[PDB]
Length: 115
Image 1 (spheres, helix red, strand yellow):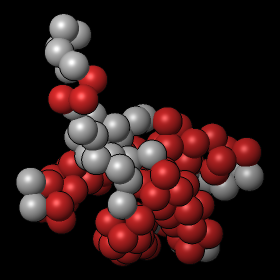
Image 2 (cartoon, rainbow, N blue to C red):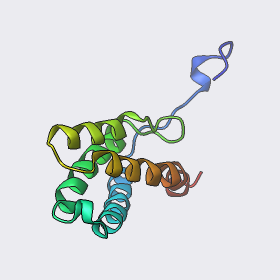
Image 3 (cartoon, rainbow, N blue to C red):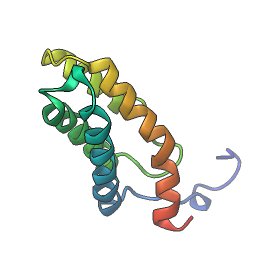
């Protein structure tokens, strides 16, 4: 954080697979509920949520180590994957995903880790 200090002074938390799993369940349940109500996703909610959830969990499991590490790239990956598979609503789903993640992930990490 401050360049003159010793590297040994800065311990950063590793990603936590149990947090990734628990937070992915909350994300999935939010996304299923939010997208289910809308004609745009009527026949594809499960598939679209499945794409978003897989990308989200993979990022939390390997890459998320608390505040300062939730990158935008998984949400770009969600829109790109939905666009590649010609699933309608890519921008809408990725925006729902990033809004929820912005609102919850760091806060939930602090609560889950007790920090």
